[PDB]
Image 1 (cartoon, one colour):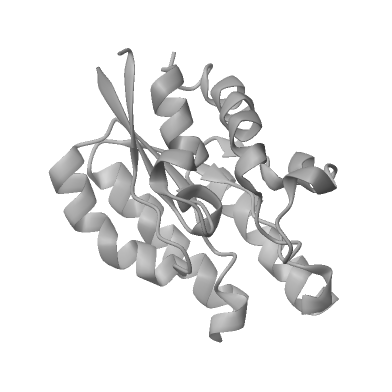
Image 2 (cartoon, helix red, strand yellow):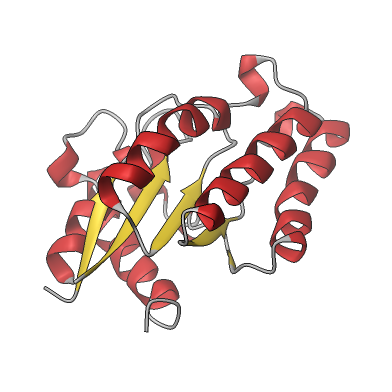
Length: 178
Protein backbone atom coordinates (compact mmCIF):
# COMPACT_ATOMS: atom_id res chain seq x y z
CA UNK A 1 0.00 0.00 0.00
CA UNK A 2 1.09 3.58 -0.63
CA UNK A 3 1.58 6.00 2.26
CA UNK A 4 -0.28 9.20 3.10
CA UNK A 5 1.68 11.28 5.59
CA UNK A 6 -0.27 13.71 7.79
CA UNK A 7 1.88 16.70 8.80
CA UNK A 8 -0.31 18.65 11.20
CA UNK A 9 -0.74 20.22 14.62
CA UNK A 10 -3.26 19.65 17.41
CA UNK A 11 -6.13 19.37 14.92
CA UNK A 12 -4.65 16.18 13.44
CA UNK A 13 -2.66 14.90 16.44
CA UNK A 14 -5.69 15.11 18.70
CA UNK A 15 -5.89 17.66 21.49
CA UNK A 16 -5.79 16.10 24.95
CA UNK A 17 -6.66 12.64 23.62
CA UNK A 18 -4.49 9.68 22.62
CA UNK A 19 -3.16 9.00 19.14
CA UNK A 20 -5.64 6.13 18.71
CA UNK A 21 -8.56 8.50 19.33
CA UNK A 22 -7.48 11.09 16.73
CA UNK A 23 -9.11 11.01 13.30
CA UNK A 24 -5.96 9.97 11.38
CA UNK A 25 -5.90 6.65 13.28
CA UNK A 26 -9.60 6.13 12.57
CA UNK A 27 -8.97 6.89 8.90
CA UNK A 28 -6.06 4.44 8.85
CA UNK A 29 -8.38 1.84 10.35
CA UNK A 30 -11.08 2.63 7.80
CA UNK A 31 -8.60 2.37 4.93
CA UNK A 32 -4.88 -2.29 3.77
CA UNK A 33 -5.16 -0.10 0.68
CA UNK A 34 -3.48 3.07 1.95
CA UNK A 35 -1.29 3.56 5.02
CA UNK A 36 -2.07 6.71 7.01
CA UNK A 37 0.95 7.87 9.04
CA UNK A 38 0.18 10.57 11.58
CA UNK A 39 3.20 12.85 12.01
CA UNK A 40 1.22 15.58 13.80
CA UNK A 41 2.24 17.19 17.11
CA UNK A 42 0.06 19.43 19.27
CA UNK A 43 1.25 23.04 19.28
CA UNK A 44 3.46 22.76 16.18
CA UNK A 45 3.89 25.89 14.07
CA UNK A 46 4.54 25.58 10.34
CA UNK A 47 8.24 26.07 11.11
CA UNK A 48 8.28 23.22 13.62
CA UNK A 49 6.59 20.98 11.05
CA UNK A 50 9.10 21.98 8.39
CA UNK A 51 11.91 21.13 10.82
CA UNK A 52 10.59 17.56 11.11
CA UNK A 53 9.79 17.10 7.41
CA UNK A 54 13.16 15.92 5.98
CA UNK A 55 13.42 12.94 8.34
CA UNK A 56 9.75 12.08 7.75
CA UNK A 57 10.09 12.06 3.96
CA UNK A 58 13.23 9.91 4.15
CA UNK A 59 11.75 7.48 6.69
CA UNK A 60 8.24 7.15 5.26
CA UNK A 61 8.74 7.88 1.54
CA UNK A 62 5.09 9.02 1.24
CA UNK A 63 3.26 9.31 -2.07
CA UNK A 64 1.07 12.08 -0.62
CA UNK A 65 1.55 14.54 2.25
CA UNK A 66 -1.40 16.34 3.86
CA UNK A 67 -0.16 19.68 5.17
CA UNK A 68 -2.33 21.04 8.00
CA UNK A 69 -0.25 23.79 9.59
CA UNK A 70 -0.19 27.52 10.22
CA UNK A 71 -2.86 27.89 12.88
CA UNK A 72 -0.30 28.17 15.68
CA UNK A 73 1.89 30.70 13.84
CA UNK A 74 0.01 33.86 14.83
CA UNK A 75 0.29 33.36 18.58
CA UNK A 76 3.94 32.38 18.11
CA UNK A 77 4.90 35.76 16.67
CA UNK A 78 4.97 34.84 12.98
CA UNK A 79 3.80 37.30 10.33
CA UNK A 80 1.64 36.01 7.44
CA UNK A 81 4.64 36.46 5.15
CA UNK A 82 6.72 34.13 7.33
CA UNK A 83 3.97 31.50 7.40
CA UNK A 84 3.73 31.75 3.61
CA UNK A 85 7.45 31.19 3.05
CA UNK A 86 7.53 28.28 5.50
CA UNK A 87 4.60 26.56 3.81
CA UNK A 88 6.17 27.33 0.44
CA UNK A 89 9.30 25.51 1.60
CA UNK A 90 7.28 22.56 2.89
CA UNK A 91 5.55 22.24 -0.48
CA UNK A 92 8.90 22.52 -2.24
CA UNK A 93 10.43 19.80 -0.06
CA UNK A 94 7.43 17.51 -0.51
CA UNK A 95 7.57 17.84 -4.30
CA UNK A 96 11.35 17.35 -4.36
CA UNK A 97 10.75 14.07 -2.53
CA UNK A 98 8.52 13.00 -5.43
CA UNK A 99 5.42 13.16 -3.24
CA UNK A 100 2.18 15.03 -3.88
CA UNK A 101 1.41 17.79 -1.36
CA UNK A 102 -2.22 18.17 -0.30
CA UNK A 103 -2.70 21.58 1.31
CA UNK A 104 -5.53 22.37 3.70
CA UNK A 105 -7.05 25.80 4.18
CA UNK A 106 -6.63 27.08 7.74
CA UNK A 107 -8.73 29.83 9.35
CA UNK A 108 -7.60 31.65 12.51
CA UNK A 109 -9.97 33.08 15.15
CA UNK A 110 -11.85 36.29 14.34
CA UNK A 111 -10.25 38.04 17.33
CA UNK A 112 -6.87 37.95 15.55
CA UNK A 113 -7.67 41.08 13.54
CA UNK A 114 -8.97 41.61 10.01
CA UNK A 115 -5.55 42.77 8.80
CA UNK A 116 -3.99 39.46 9.84
CA UNK A 117 -6.95 37.19 9.03
CA UNK A 118 -7.25 38.41 5.44
CA UNK A 119 -3.52 38.05 4.78
CA UNK A 120 -3.28 34.70 6.58
CA UNK A 121 -6.28 33.16 4.81
CA UNK A 122 -4.99 34.33 1.42
CA UNK A 123 -1.78 32.35 1.88
CA UNK A 124 -3.39 28.99 1.12
CA UNK A 125 -5.19 29.75 -2.16
CA UNK A 126 -2.03 31.52 -3.37
CA UNK A 127 0.29 28.58 -2.70
CA UNK A 128 -2.18 26.02 -4.06
CA UNK A 129 -2.20 28.01 -7.29
CA UNK A 130 1.55 28.59 -7.23
CA UNK A 131 2.30 24.87 -6.88
CA UNK A 132 -0.82 23.68 -8.72
CA UNK A 133 -1.84 21.45 -5.81
CA UNK A 134 -5.16 20.39 -4.23
CA UNK A 135 -6.47 22.80 -1.60
CA UNK A 136 -8.83 21.04 0.80
CA UNK A 137 -11.39 23.08 2.73
CA UNK A 138 -10.62 23.56 6.44
CA UNK A 139 -12.24 20.50 8.03
CA UNK A 140 -13.10 22.44 11.20
CA UNK A 141 -15.71 24.61 9.46
CA UNK A 142 -18.22 21.73 9.64
CA UNK A 143 -17.17 20.84 13.18
CA UNK A 144 -17.78 24.40 14.48
CA UNK A 145 -21.45 23.94 13.53
CA UNK A 146 -21.82 21.21 16.16
CA UNK A 147 -21.04 22.51 19.67
CA UNK A 148 -21.33 18.91 20.86
CA UNK A 149 -18.18 18.17 18.82
CA UNK A 150 -16.13 21.05 20.26
CA UNK A 151 -13.91 20.95 23.33
CA UNK A 152 -14.24 23.68 26.00
CA UNK A 153 -11.69 26.03 24.41
CA UNK A 154 -13.93 26.43 21.37
CA UNK A 155 -10.88 25.65 19.25
CA UNK A 156 -10.24 21.90 19.18
CA UNK A 157 -12.63 19.10 18.12
CA UNK A 158 -13.43 16.58 20.87
CA UNK A 159 -13.34 12.78 20.91
CA UNK A 160 -16.90 12.42 19.59
CA UNK A 161 -15.94 14.52 16.56
CA UNK A 162 -13.09 12.31 15.40
CA UNK A 163 -15.13 9.61 13.63
CA UNK A 164 -16.97 12.27 11.67
CA UNK A 165 -13.80 14.11 10.71
CA UNK A 166 -12.35 10.78 9.58
CA UNK A 167 -15.36 10.19 7.30
CA UNK A 168 -15.22 13.77 6.02
CA UNK A 169 -11.51 13.36 5.26
CA UNK A 170 -12.01 9.99 3.61
CA UNK A 171 -14.50 11.68 1.26
CA UNK A 172 -12.21 14.61 0.47
CA UNK A 173 -9.14 12.39 0.00
CA UNK A 174 -10.80 9.57 -1.98
CA UNK A 175 -10.52 11.35 -5.36
CA UNK A 176 -6.95 12.44 -4.61
CA UNK A 177 -5.50 9.06 -3.62
CA UNK A 178 -7.48 7.20 -6.30
